[PDB]
Image (cartoon, rainbow, N blue to C red):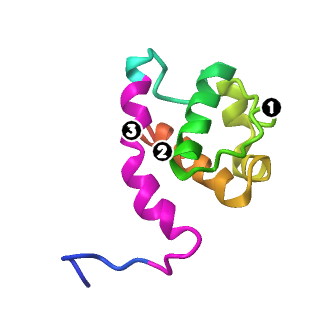
Amino acid sequence: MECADVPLLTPSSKEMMSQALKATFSGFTKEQQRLGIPKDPRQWTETHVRDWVMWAVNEFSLKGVDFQKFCMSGAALCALGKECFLELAPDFVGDILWEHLEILQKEDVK
């Protein structure tokens, strides 16, 4: 068990979000509060969802997201589920966003 610098998985596809996303999540969620944007997703507007949508995206330079495919009100954002969301973006980006989607809600995940 390496505790100094813990090795995870093969840094090709997902390891990027593993280190980058899970750490960076505090970024939007911090200004989310500032923007008066509710911490959870299931009550967002199309604006709030897309804000957070393009955030994990713009961080990763996933900036080829179809904002129209990403037209979710927060309840819709939630309603899609992983299945839909990841088909709703590139399979990495959907889960990238889906992670933070889950992360926003993980602040109250039970």
Q: Residue at 74% of width from left, 34% of height from top?
A: 67
Element under label 2? helix
Mark 1 → mark 2, Cα distance in angstroms: 23 Å
Residue that label 1 marks? 68
Mark 3 → mark 1, Cα distance in angstroms: 24 Å
Nearest to viewer (mark 2 / mark 3)? 3
Q: Residue at 65% of width from left, 45% of height from top?
A: 63
- Does residue 16 belong to the magenta stretch? yes
Magenta range: 9-32
Q: Is residue 107 left or right of residue 40?
A: left
Residue 12 visible to the viewer: yes
Nearest to viewer (mark 1 / mark 2)? 1
Considering every residue shown, the one lying at the far left of the view is 4
Q: Residue 13: x percent and y percent?
A: 59, 71
Mark 2 → mark 3, Cα distance in angstroms: 12 Å
Q: What's the mark number on residue 56?
A: none
| Amino acid, disc 2 | Ile
From what the image shows, is residue 1 above or below residue 80? below
- Work out whether residue 103 or residue 36 is closer to the camera in this orientation and state it: 36
Q: Sequence order check: which comes first, mark 2 or mark 3?
A: 3
Query: Quadrant location of residue 81?
Result: top right
